[PDB]
Amino acid sequence: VSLDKAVIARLRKGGEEFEVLVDPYLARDLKEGKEVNFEDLLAAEEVFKDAKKGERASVDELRKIFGTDDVFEIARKIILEGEVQITAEQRREMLEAKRKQIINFISRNTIDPAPHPPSRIERALEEAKVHIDIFKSVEAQVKDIVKALKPILPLKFEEMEIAIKIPPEHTGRAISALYNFGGVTREEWQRDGSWICVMRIPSGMYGDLMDLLGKVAKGEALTKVLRRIG
């Protein structure tokens, strides 16, 4: 990351200011909980007292304050505990992207006692003035958001277990694909060359599963709903 695209992440500790120049997208990833290659994250491998003036913190002061001189370790603490100074445009773009993943996750993993199209979810997020955290993964905030939409959009998180049996002819074009869809369990080849499994999927993906089946096994697959798990 070039110093011209890098942003400052700052932390005030023991009466002093500490800064690092980082790739804002990789810093967002760290605050979210993802694994980050620090070699790509830091625009410069050092801790600053003032990054804009180029004032470098000294090894002795780093040891006293942080109890270590390791730049990656210090940078991690600054990014997690301090503030990442992203631009308004970066904040806008990150917000737009996190909103999308949230809407997509909700649509695919819920149904309405069956799945709401994304636009229905979109509208409801607006109507309820839901706050979206750009530094948190979808998984970490998707339950407060859902129980915030509770009053105006009925939403239920649910998975289904569906038994599947593929005719001997289609096990070539159907087994690889189902694994690609995700959810295959208890798979097992059969006497006659047929194959069976139990698909575990988000109920909002049921229509996609049946559509995939029809295509890969040409209406030949057999299915049976075993249970719905909330």
Image (tube, helix red, strand yellow):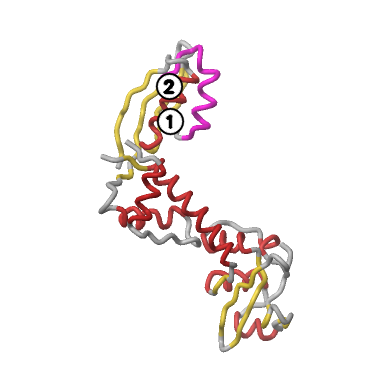
Q: Earlier in the sequence, mark 1 or mark 2?
A: 2
Element marked by disc 1? helix
Q: Residue 196: which disc?
A: 2
- Three-letter residue code for mark 2: Ile
Quadrant occupied by the N terminus: bottom right
* Mark 1, residue position: 208
Q: Residue at the location (64% across, 77% down)? A: 19
Task: State the image coordinates of residue 126 (x, y, percent, origin top left).
Answer: 37, 55
Q: Residue at the location (62% across, 58% down)? A: 36
- The answer to which quarter of the image holds residue 157 is top left
Q: How crowded is mark 1: few (under 14 residues within 10 Å), some or many (20 or more)?
A: few
Q: Residue at the location (45% across, 31% down)? A: 184
Q: Is residue 59 visible?
A: no
Task: State the image coordinates of residue 195 (x, y, percent, origin top left).
Answer: 46, 19
What is the span of residues highlighted in magenta in the rendered image?
Answer: 165-182
Element marked by disc 2? strand
Is 125 inside the magenta-drawn segment?
Answer: no
Q: Residue 150: which disc?
A: none
Asked if 112 appears above or below 226 in the picture, the reply is below
Task: State the image coordinates of residue 159 (x, y, percent, origin top left).
Answer: 35, 38
Q: Which of 108 and 37 is in front in this view?
A: 108
Quadrant occupied by the C terminus: top left
Along the horizontal axis of the image, is 204 left or right of 78? left
Task: State the image coordinates of residue 189 (x, y, percent, origin top left).
Answer: 47, 19
Q: Which of 154 and 223 is in front in this view?
A: 154
Q: Residues within 10 Å of mark 2 (few under 14, many from 20)?
A: many
Q: Nearer the viewer, residue 171 or 91?
A: 91
Which callout, 1 or 2, points to the residue nearer the camera? Answer: 1
Asked if 175 appears above or below 35 in the picture, the reply is above
